[PDB]
Amino acid sequence: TPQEAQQVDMWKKYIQWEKSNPLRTEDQTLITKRVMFAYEQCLLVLGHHPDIWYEAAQYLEQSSKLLAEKGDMNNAKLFSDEAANIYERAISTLLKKNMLLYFAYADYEESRMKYEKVHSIYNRLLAIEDIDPTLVYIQYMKFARRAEGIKSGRMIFKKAREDARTRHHVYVTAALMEYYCSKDKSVAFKIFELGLKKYGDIPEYVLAYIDYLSHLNEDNNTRVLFERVLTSGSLPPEKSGEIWARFLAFESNIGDLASILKVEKRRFTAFREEYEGKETALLVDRYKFMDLYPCSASELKALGYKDV
Amino acid sequence: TPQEAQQVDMWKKYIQWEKSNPLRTEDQTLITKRVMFAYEQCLLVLGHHPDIWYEAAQYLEQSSKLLAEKGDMNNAKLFSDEAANIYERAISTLLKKNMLLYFAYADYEESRMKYEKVHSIYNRLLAIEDIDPTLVYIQYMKFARRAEGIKSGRMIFKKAREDARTRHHVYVTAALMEYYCSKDKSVAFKIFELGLKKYGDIPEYVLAYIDYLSHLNEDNNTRVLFERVLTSGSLPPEKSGEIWARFLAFESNIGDLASILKVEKRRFTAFREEYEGKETALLVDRYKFMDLYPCSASELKALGYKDV
Image (cartoon, rainbow over all chains, first blue to last red; front, side, top):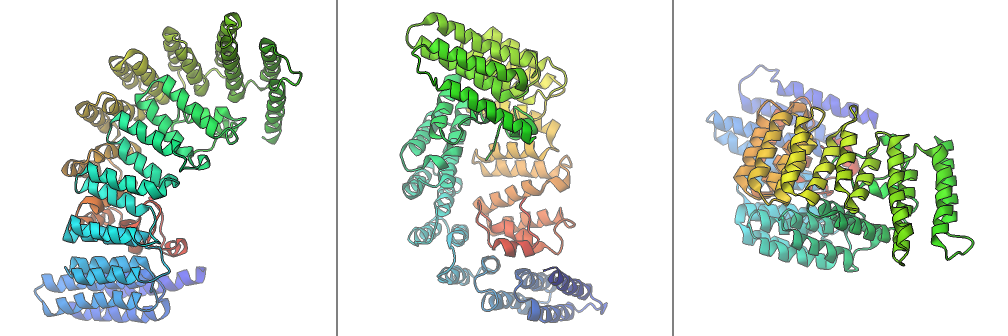
């Protein structure tokens, strides 16, 4: 609502004034106390805004940093700990399923080295039945690996495959992790293959896999994967649109005109209904390269051309 | 214009009807003529619709294949050379500078081994002063590679650079060609570097480079590239949005929380204006993964979140 936008601004503009140390004081612990009081007053009527909680926690974070740099250690801990309580209150009441704050809180405790504290935050979220954990497992994995090594990440991945709610993105994340961090193509291939087993009918997963393999730059292996995913019967034709496109493109970069036309023919087959009476529309994707088109916009729509 | 569209559809149907050979005749060359006569009358008034020319040119090419597939060589060649003149007529009259047709023409003549003919078409087009040759050179190089070889491709790439109208896309194409075909990273690097001098300010080109390098999976090199791309003044700050997200994503994949936050701080520092009092919206990009967001679309809305 437009009216609420104004409340949020009066609060933020007011908190800003408070942050500009009106007292002209120098006792940082006193400024921070006045600023927090303001945030509190704000949270009483805007407790449903993730940003309010986040910025407040962010403030105690920067504050604690200042008192530390300026020697004061006692208040550096009090404010550091208070920040974490901000996150706790956030997810413990008004925003119980807010992934954004859970992740912020996780990162904050990770920065403070409280790894067990982190583990309990992610798992706390996961234990909430009505949410899509996919993105949660990903963050969790990135944390395990980052702070406890490969083996730790793998355990989180395993916990992810065993959760019925997890979706395909988790396999992509795991496979690439093995490839980028472990520098291990062998396992990358294994996890992708494993995910292809249950998500061979999801174009974004298949495309995700196709893409990883393409960049290895070994023409043959790449062609096999293309054939396998397109010709296994797992991926419906109505959804193979971009796979065909990618395949065409691939044959264009390192193949020959016979490979290209041949593939473009198999696609027309798959969409004998779709691109019917519009072969010219399909022809465009044979020439377009990142924002460059064989025809003008108006000319391009008069062909009935639509692009992914 | 609705009127225009109605007529095309109208004629396409007729032409199509004539293609069904409503009066069952085992005389193809006659079915063809009847269909071509239909096309001809259509091209007489709708010569400005590329699809009509191409589709007609295709039918002939197919009729030439059905006749040649039964022994009748005479008509096979007759209809083949006929298809070619349809392209020839299409670019010589109403669509003098239409890329899709020149490419389709070139491609057709190429499938018939008429390479000199091909070279002529690409050149007749490049010969036209007011057009964007970029995509024309890209296609020419592709042809030059498959038909005459890598040494030939590099030749078209030279002309492409020599031409003051060309845009960055040609460098990306050459660089990747050297990578995907020549399997030569050393040259891919030079071309990309060569190009980087002329287009360090074009986010599209830079992202293309980063992406190529990034997939080579050598951490420190990728990092160095990011630092150069984002650090030299060549890239207008307001157009760095995406590069910074790639950078943050990159660190998120293979680095620790510190480097992640370090890059996030630099991103913010380069956008104080942009995302101000909207720090939370940026935090979103720290977690998002290929279509999975930490918040609900509406929640993302309130944060003033836009996707770079």
